[PDB]
Amino acid sequence: GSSGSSGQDFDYFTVDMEKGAKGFGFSIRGGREYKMDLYVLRLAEDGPAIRNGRMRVGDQIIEINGESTRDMTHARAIELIKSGGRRVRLLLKRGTGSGPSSG
Image (cartoon, rainbow, N blue to C red; front, side, top):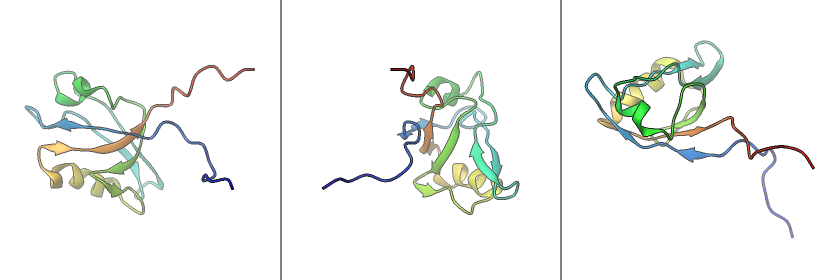
């Protein structure tokens, strides 16, 4: 009587931010175009992104605006952030882990 998928990935948390002076103030990298997942290229020091926190530079985006980030190209994810509007919600997880793995 057990239940649970296989593969204990990092913390699957969602991100919530709005548009700024020159946009959300965040970029992405990778994609089907390069045969790799979508990560956060960099962050805007003076943008609403770097102020959000939920998302940082060096993470892996598994979801974007609630749209499964699969079989998608860096171009798509780029249009999704502008397709939603001023508010963009993507699922990101920090590679910090659950803590010290020892015992």
